[PDB]
Length: 294
Ligand SMILES: Nc1nc2c(ncn2[C@@H]2O[C@H](COP(=O)(O)OP(=O)(O)NP(=O)(O)O)[C@@H](O)[C@H]2O)c(=O)[nH]1
Image (tube, rainbow, N blue to C red):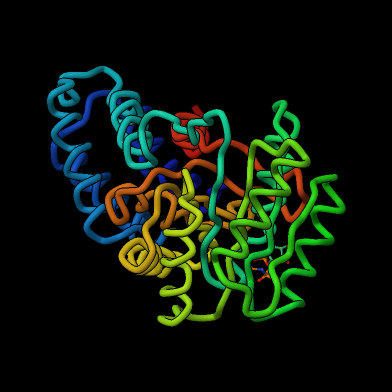
């Protein structure tokens, strides 16, 4: 997945095993390599510096200098940092009796796609999802989700042009009632850049609908930019969880490894393909070990 950084963090570590015992000087050289790999992987400079410093201390604490095989100690420490950096323990939205989630993000984020992926994912977990195209301005946008739902066998309610939040709430509540939906997914309008008027309307909707979760969908290939947007969305509307899409095309992994510190939000899911099935719960442990070959 993160082959680039992987192969990179590999030479750095693999450059210590066959040596047999290592000196602090050699350790600093390795850490610099590691630190450079992270920066080159678009990892928030701050996160990258902290990472290597953490590895340094942890490494010394593990008596690395006093080891017949340091390359391994450095491996365990670096794996621990990646794991923590990625989020630590795996998390997932907690489902209740009835759930109503919002999907937010900018255009080309994978938002709408992820919307169907969630409906399909939870449809196979014994849920009855309802997809809703919340874009009140563009009919072509609601149309893209109407098709997707038709593809994953999940009903879709499309709001009207300029429909009010209350009207949308009434309509959505009634459908869920008559069709027995327990998971209600609201795909909100996707725009190129942050649109203040839209945020206002999303805030009002958030107020009228009262979503249990507000998932912001970010395209992982946009690097650190996805984090500045995540902050914007959190400050302007309010985020509860993240979804990293296009991770299969993500050669660096800067956004993934920086979301924790930068946004302080948990990454619930990871997009791994353009197909409705291309979704899976975010597993920090998995990726951490994967990046190192563990
Ligand atoms: N490789 C890959 N492509 C993805 C993934 N998720 C979505 N895509 C692709 O990215 C493109 C944009 O997705 P999407 O955001 O749903 O399209 P949009 O019309 O901009 N809708 P929105 O308003 O929600 O942003 C689509 O061509 C979709 O197939 C993923 O996990 N991996």
